[PDB]
Image (cartoon, rainbow, N blue to C red; front, top):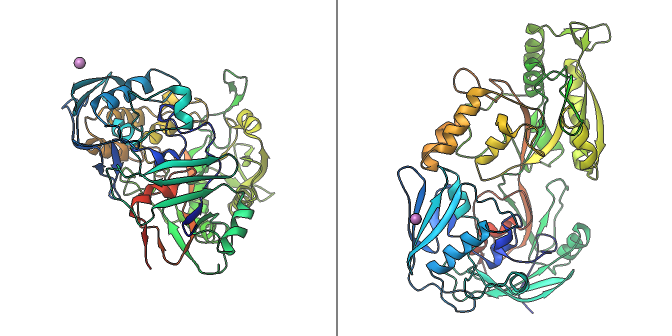
Length: 497
Ligand code: NI
């Protein structure tokens, strides 16, 4: 051996076929999309010399670099790009191509993309869908023996065991200091055990584990979009959805409750106690992103402010020391998913933090199936996070209300809907950004704390790794909520010795 062994996620089952989407994170190892995001969130082109949307944002012009090749040496041209997009759309998978219509090849280095309607977020598709070879693609065969333009290529794959890959010599981006990589697939505990023993060069660890010194290893803290928040029902009770699930909560429908909970919680204390300080306070679902409203942050852990907000809206302390309004006491149930000690620790901590302002929080846990039934009538603990601004839409659009796990509190604000649609219809993502910011607050209304306060956002989680002292994991964009997020920086990895 003498090569780098890594433990950063679990088995890449199902396979490595870009036609099945970017839902998994391992694909970034063997494949490369047309675009690669920068740390300043602009876009670099690995395979493109030129890419330009039209004034209406309905068409894209793509120009390839001339001598590109696949991992097997076969040439990468317009034919393969157009094939990739047309067939990814034309199958499932059900890759969400959005408003994508079709891809036309102009010449071997040029491709024209056609859309149904303006989509400012389509760039996120360009930096996501991996390129596939038109000549050599077979649906069943490709998952097991894939051909890609990624930084590495498959050498061997041992199920439930390990994966061996080597550097792709035809890679169009930067080569790193590591010629060969072996990825080990282990449960967290055995992984940590192998890490201390110095068998591994890089290992992902949970931010919640009071990590002590590890022999001949160093701790890396990488930024992430992964977050934690509480979603409130915004409507009164009494109605039910298509599944017969109850909709609404007579307590959390009052905006004063949601604002008060937003101010009472001390997020820094959450980060330090539960996440061992490896988290950042989050006041929005898009904290740390360009499309976050710059005026969205608040000074929290203010019991007095919370009590003021509650008093001004008619929520008064009863004899039991619990808030009450028009004969209705503030007693609410917080739901969360079982199977995680940390989620529960977070929940109980929240109950304890809401006790001083007179809100009595009962806690219930269950399987996703169980949570689903109660998810619309009670406050609920969720984890999300995405590098696509589209998530704002999924959270706050009236059209997304009750759609799967999105917008379960049935939040509807027509002005917010307008800002959202304006944002989607913008010809470029840059022009879209100011409208995305208007969602929190436009000066009059919004979905944020200054406005309707649909959420109580708690934290943005950061990912933590142990790495051999001679290993430099470099730098990159915030890591996704998923496995193999570290791979987003893989090209900048260096060897310090
Ligand atoms: Ni055409």
